[PDB]
Amino acid sequence: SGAIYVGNYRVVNRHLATHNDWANLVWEDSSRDLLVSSTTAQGCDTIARCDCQTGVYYCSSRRKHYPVSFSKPSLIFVEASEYYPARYQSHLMLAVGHSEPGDCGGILRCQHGVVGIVSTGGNGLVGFADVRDLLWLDE
Ligand SMILES: Cc1cccc(NC(=O)N2CCC[C@H](C(N)=O)C2)c1
Ligand SMILES: [Zn+2]
């Protein structure tokens, strides 16, 4: 679990979004596994605007932060689940590192701020949904 709170927005994995999130929907994209909902309180997370390929992510299944080199956002095939059929998830970045399903929502950060959130994993790999291109989260 986990979310990004920036201004009046909450960013979560679309597969983990609650009834509240859907009832206060701003934007959702199944192909990215992202959903943004409106909030009443202020969010102070800073979103990174960059092309960094190194950062640190939070891994709840280990209660630890790990440094990673990750790939540029791209279309990567994702195996079927109780949330989605087999498909290409876009805006996805992979890194070598530990992850388990409950790790989704853990934040990936670089020196410039929040980069994305854990969305996929398996076989010694961890996949992050990029949020750096969503420039509207700041205005
Ligand atoms: C982080 C992690 C580790 C091991 C396994 C998983 N499950 C995973 O990748 N799935 C199921 C949940 C929805 C994901 C998706 N974005 O389509 C696909 C996650
Ligand atoms: Zn950066």
Image: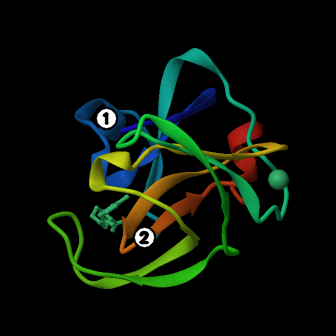
At which x and y percent is residue 20? 30, 30
At which x and y percent is residue 66? 59, 48
Q: Does the image show residue 29?
A: no
Q: Secondary structure at mark 1?
A: helix
Q: Earlier in the sequence, mark 1 or mark 2?
A: 1
Picture layout, residue 102 above or below residue 9: below
Q: Nearer the viewer, mark 1 or mark 2?
A: 2
How many marks can you see? Answer: 2
Which residue is rendered at x = 27% and y = 37% of the image? Answer: 18
Numbered circle sitting on residue 23: 1
Which residue is rendered at x = 68% and y = 29% of the image? Answer: 45
Residue 12's quadrant in the figure? top left
Q: Is residue 139 left or right of residue 90?
A: right
Pick the front one: 69 or 10: 69
Quadrant the N terminus occupies: top left
- Give the residue type at disc 1: Ala
- Give the residue type at disc 2: Gly
Residue beneath label 2, please?
124
Crowd rating for badge 2 (residues with CA inside 10 Å; few <14, some 14–19, many 20+): few
Which residue is rendered at x = 74% and y = 42% of the image? Answer: 47
Q: Does the image show residue 132?
A: yes
Residue 124's quadrant in the figure? bottom left
